[PDB]
Image: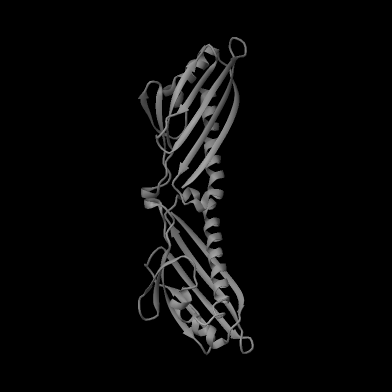
Length: 158
Length: 153
C-alpha cells in the first residue's frame, strides 16, 4: 500500500589497503556483519543472498523489509555490483561499491544503492510516511559506512 | 504504537432557538447523524454510546478509531458533556457543548473535545504521523460543525 523509492550515494576513505578493503566488501556475509539491524542473511549459493531486516514492530501491524540480490565482484576493475532477484520479498534492491587505492594503506570507496521498498501501510499516509522511511534508510547506511570505516582497527574485520 | 493527543475548541452561532439547538445536540443519535465517516454508533444504554469510525486502510494493517463516551445533559445550565468509558476501543475522548441564548431565535455554541488516540503504527512514525491524525480529526470536526449549522435550516 506504500512504495518508497530510494537512490543514494556515499563517499568515504577506509584506512586499509586496497586488497583488504576489496576482500571484505566482496565477502557479503562478512560485510553484512557491519550492517545494522539485519535479522537474517540467507546464503542462497551462487553469489545470491536474501536479506531479512529486523521487523517493526507489533504483531499483525508489524512490517519487515525482505529482499534478495545477486552479487558480482571484479577485483581488477575495482567494482562490486548487486542486482535484484525478481519476485522475492517486498524490496527491489541494486547497488555497487567502486574502490581504488589511495596509497598503500587506504582505499577510496564509493557506495551506491537504489531501492524500492513496498510496505503494507495506508496509502492515505504515503506523503507523510515515505520521508521517514527514507530518512531511516539513510541513517542505517550512514551507520554501515561508519562501521566499515572502523573494521580494520582491528585484527578481525567482521 | 503511537498515541496522538488532541485538544480543540470551536465557536459557532446557530440561527435557531435555544430549545431547538440544545435538543438536537443533546440527542446523540440525531446529532451523530451529522458527523462524517461514522461506521457505527452503538447504544450502550444509560446515555452511553460507542463510536466506530470508518477504517483506514486495508486488511490486517488497517487502523480504525473506536471510542465510547457517557453523555450528560443539563439544559438548565446550558451544558452537555461526555466522559470516556475506560477500556473501550483505542481512543479516550471527553468533551462538551456549552450553549447560551443570543435572543429568542439565535444560540451561541461552544464545542470542546479532548481526545487521546492510540493507533497501531510503528512508533518510528510518531513525529510525522501525529500532525496528520490531528489534521484529519480537525477536518472531521469542521465538517461536523458545518453539517449541524446546515441541519438547522
